[PDB]
Length: 135
Ligand SMILES: Cc1cn([C@H]2C[C@H](OP(=O)(O)O)[C@@H](COP(=O)(O)O)O2)c(=O)[nH]c1=O
Ligand SMILES: [Ca+2]
Image (cartoon, rainbow, N blue to C red; front, side):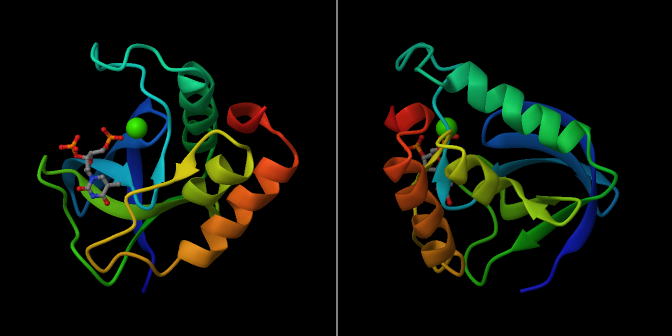
């Protein structure tokens, strides 16, 4: 795996962000995690949805340098969203969210599991701390 530069365009919610990647605007969805819903009327505004959103926004907006890291499997979902680990000044947004108890490990499939144990450990620790979602 390798990290590639990208530029923030807009934070959309906890786990979805719009980036400039290789000169073209693209929506990215964070690999191996799920933040709670804030947009879809089916699920409603889920608990910690706004908090996950604000955390991701601050993390990406405040960063000097954004990088995307594709995994070894499928690189886009069915909705055209790029699937990657996003880093803000070298810190993984996906891991930060899980460790903060603001996303759960989810959707681990289609070859994209390089960071699974890293993220599962973060989750176990957030759970032990009864932090946010696990409170
Ligand atoms: C994270 C991730 C999500 N998805 C899809 C599965 C879900 O599709 P369906 O909604 O069609 O079931 C959706 C969950 O993302 P959201 O949490 O952004 O809704 O995104 C993937 O296909 N691959 C992935 O790696
Ligand atoms: Ca989500």
